[PDB]
Length: 324
Length: 283
Ligand SMILES: O=P(O)(O)C(O)(Cn1ccnc1)P(=O)(O)O
Ligand SMILES: C=C(C)CCOP(=O)(O)OP(=O)(O)O
Ligand SMILES: [Mg+2]
Ligand SMILES: [Mg+2]
Ligand SMILES: [Mg+2]
Image 1 (cartoon, rainbow over the protein chains, first blue to last red):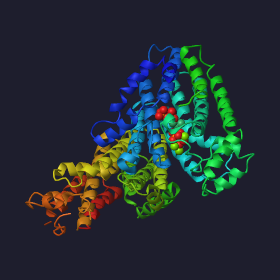
Image 2 (tube, rainbow over the protein chains, first blue to last red; image 1 turned 90 degrees about the horizontal axis):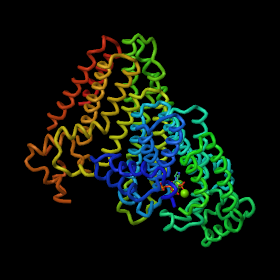
Image 3 (cartoon, each protein chain N blue to C red; image 1 turned 180 degrees about the vertical axis):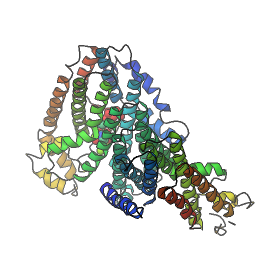
Image 4 (cartoon, chains in turn yellow, cyan; image 1 turned 30 degrees about the vertical axis):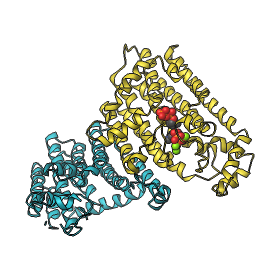
């Protein structure tokens, strides 16, 4: 249960959840309702939780009695950047279901959804500049660039089966892992801990996020749309060749033709899907997630033994057992 | 896309620094306000923050137009994928994001939190207001101040921020910087309402009733009638106001000129003074 997993920082999340409503304002009922749609749809709030967990462990190590106001704002900032990414991702992937509810672009047109994401990006970087830490300012600005860089790169290698796993991990760093890595390090920065601790907190966030996206790519093959709350079996059909396919593409070369066919033949997608399950593609991709999770756990031993650290120890083990 | 705007900008800024020795509008304002405030502060050359502020602003302006043209398909139950391939939707949003991201990334690397607070604010209200623009179309109940505010967020606010951050990067007094925000706001409004005139002389066909139409809809007893709807379909000529539309810009323009009087006599302060005059010269 994600509820029990995030128990030690449950109270911190409830303050954030009651606060995202006003995080955009009230002058614009369209933008307000567009935000209530995706915020109220029921996200997992995993990115604010890790910020909360890292902020507390590194605050105990630094002698702070409570959390700074910039800790609690940072958690609201990362979630709003994550939300802005999802909005722009759905317009890109032509997805009509997010978190069990209809996506914004199919309610208010693609333009308003794009502007809502543009607003959420500038809004978070505006809050972030008001936190006055210049180092976090540049770090998060790098992440906003990484989301666009990965999406342009992911859009240009579709149906290209000679894509390497090296490219696949770099792509998933840009669009998913860079934000999570910057959020865990920026939390350590607002606690004032040493540079080495700052660096290892960033290394936990990038490796947990890397395996997190690998699992997100697995659940597209192994879970239903109703289960995930978002369209399932969509990456392969669009030409986005995730780790199960790249692993599978090494032994069963019939995949190459079907994907280079752009699945034009009727029945081709159904047979290509079973060719992925045919091979050890799904399980070989899972062990890539386990390895990325192994590196993430090692970065935690720099911290003392605390239930904040052991929850952060549990969050990768929860990733490998997650049906979403 | 991003790499192409910087090229013709790096060249256009040189074509002006060469002309100053003995679109293109936004970095010209940054360049001339940068040097005017620079010589006042004892800076013998434009710093790097001034040079890369000019490309920051145009990248925001250009990325704005790209995202503003994203298609509305709300009530489309036909072929969504066909119109998006036809109008390059997925390409437009990705390039606009990357241009928006590289701009704030440049801005973040300048290590001035006051400019970052100001610029991100400009983008924020641009996105919010453009979401709200759907309602104000076909609405009789806007005042002249409500029009100047939508026209601020649309264009004028970005120009005012560019001219004040140019003064901030010269490290001069905050009163001269505040006067530099005032040069841009006004010239921006004065530039927006003169653009709103040029089209009508369609923008009301979609429902954008600018300052000409609000100086009307007052005298013109009805007017609201026609815009209340298809109707007589004729009379869609207009009525036609413009006297209070070429004077509205003339008044804002002389407020911008008045803000330049804190700067000493210089070839940049006079070129900036001629910027307002050249905007009204299109009459
Ligand atoms: O599969 P995607 O990477 O597009 C996704 O994980 C979202 N996303 C977008 C960028 N990083 C992650 P989602 O499946 O939620 O649609
Ligand atoms: C980066 C991608 C994988 C986001 C989707 O997974 P999440 O589980 O993090 O999305 P929400 O719960 O917040 O809706
Ligand atoms: Mg995607
Ligand atoms: Mg997607
Ligand atoms: Mg996915």
